[PDB]
Image (cartoon, coloured by chain):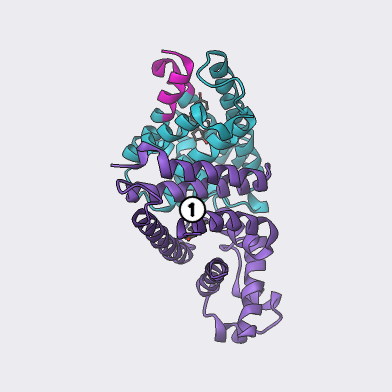
Chain colours: A cyan, B purple
């Protein structure tokens, strides 16, 4: 509860001031913990961020058993569960808020950004594996262009998150995300321009 | 009106290298090789430079429309917008700043409000293209236009965001037309965008 208390203080501070303008010492103030104890648990600020990203991912994967007839069906559930969690889980809300809006791509953030890309590369391969299992079960056609489909998926879903935050949550994500996900899946299943 | 454009581009250039939050007027005026006062005459603050930059992006897009049916004109304008992102350094840098170097902190609050104003304008313009397209029967009378405009913007936002934040990992020239085609098809045919 010491290591956790520090990450939530990192998250709360990142959300307030942004990643670049946040210091390993002002995180200590929020957590109310000596810097040597902080250094005990994490080397530097990228570490706090890497742990926040890992917690987000753990939460998604831990629920996948509870989301799970067939794996392409599980994907649908996991996508829908993701967007509900954005609304109702304050940790996932703030973290994605930070990732899309509070993490500017300047040299000051270079190390944090490389951490983001490590986790996104893991997610990119998660998608490929799901597409691959789905072709094998014949939920997707055998000539599905998997490299293109992966860009299409990340593009479609990133766009909805970006739009939602940028608008200031000015539309109902609970009604809109299922429409968007519905259209996307239909396109992966049926549209010719995602075939090789 | 040519002094204004030189001050504007020094800001765009400085915003691109440092981001908006860390740029100061001093550095802009320096980059432009003019005094603080002379900059101040044309532009009071960074908000006003960013606003003018955003205004010039929109002017470029609108001027090229002026040179089929409007629903066909829309498709062409989406396609050319993404070509322009590759081949036009000002549209590249600007959208790079808007999506990657425009943090949503309190110091940037005024710039963000600027950005929302222009995004609102574009939303109204998209809403009109959909309204005209319906009456010309390029889209169905039953088209859910409120959802459709969210759908169009997040489709395009997603491409731009994904291309910039991945370090331009894929070829926008092959990807953008394929995304825009699929979008166009869904607007015309997908039943999720109706009723
Ligand atoms: C699509 C995203 C990457 C891939 C993620 C994934 C990847 C595999 C999987 O089985 C489920 C999910 C759900 C959340 C998805 C993410 C939501 C937004 C992000 O871009
Ligand atoms: C979707 C955007 C706003 C609406 C823009 C528009 C709005 C109306 C129109 O007739 C054409 C275009 C092309 C470019 C579009 C933009 C590309 C990026 C921007 O977010």
Q: Residue, x 46% and y 47% (percent of image)?
A: B154
- Queried whether the magenta region covers residue A77, the answer comes back as yes
Q: Main secondary structure of the magenta part?
A: helix
Q: Residue, x 36% and y 48% (percent of image)?
A: A169
Quadrant in the rendering for residue B30: bottom right
Quadrant in the rendering for residue B169: top right
Q: Quadrant of the C terminus of chain B?
A: top left
Numbered label tally: 1
Q: Quadrant of the N terminus of chain B?
A: bottom right
Please identify the residue farthest to the left as the structure is shown: B195
Residue A143 point in image, percent of width and height: 62, 23
Taking the image as shown, residue B173 lies to the left or right of residue B161, namely: right
Taking the image as shown, residue A149 lies to the left or right of residue A79, namely: right
Task: Name the foreground residue: A117 vs A78.
Answer: A78
Circle 1 is placed at which residue position?
A17
| Residue stretch rendered in magenta on the structure | A61-79
Cβ(mark 1) to ligand 1 < 8 Å?
no
Residue A89 at least partly seen = no
Quadrant in the rendering for residue A66: top left
Task: Name the foreground residue: A100 vs A138.
Answer: A138
Residue B165 point in image, percent of width and height: 61, 46
Residue B38 point in image, percent of width and height: 61, 86
- In the image, residue A41 above or below residue B185: above
């Amino acid at each position: 509860k010491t290591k956790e208390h520090l990450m939530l203080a990192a998250l709360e501070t990142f959300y307030r001031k942004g990643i670049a303008r946040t210091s390993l010492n002002e995180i200590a103030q929020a957590a109310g913990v000596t810097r040597g104890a902080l250094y005990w648990h994490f080397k530097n600020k990228e570490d706090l961020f890497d742990a926040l990203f890992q917690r987000i991912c753990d939460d998604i994967e831990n629920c996948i058993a509870q989301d799970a007839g067939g794996s392409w069906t599980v994907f649908r559930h996991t996508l829908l569960h993701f967007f509900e969690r954005l609304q109702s889980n304050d940790i996932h809300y703030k973290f994605h808020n930070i990732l899309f809006l509070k993490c500017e791509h300047t040299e000051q953030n270079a190390a944090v950004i490389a951490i983001a890309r490590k986790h996104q590369a893991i997610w990119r391969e998660k998608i490929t594996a799901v597409l691959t299992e789905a072709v094998e079960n014949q939920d997707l056609a055998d000539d599905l262009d998997k490299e293109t489909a992966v860009i299409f998926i990340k593009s479609t879903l990133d766009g909805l998150i970006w739009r939602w935050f940028s608008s200031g949550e000015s539309f109902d994500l609970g009604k809109t995300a299922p429409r968007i996900i519905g259209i996307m899946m239909d396109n992966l299943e049926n549209h010719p321009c995602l075939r090789r």
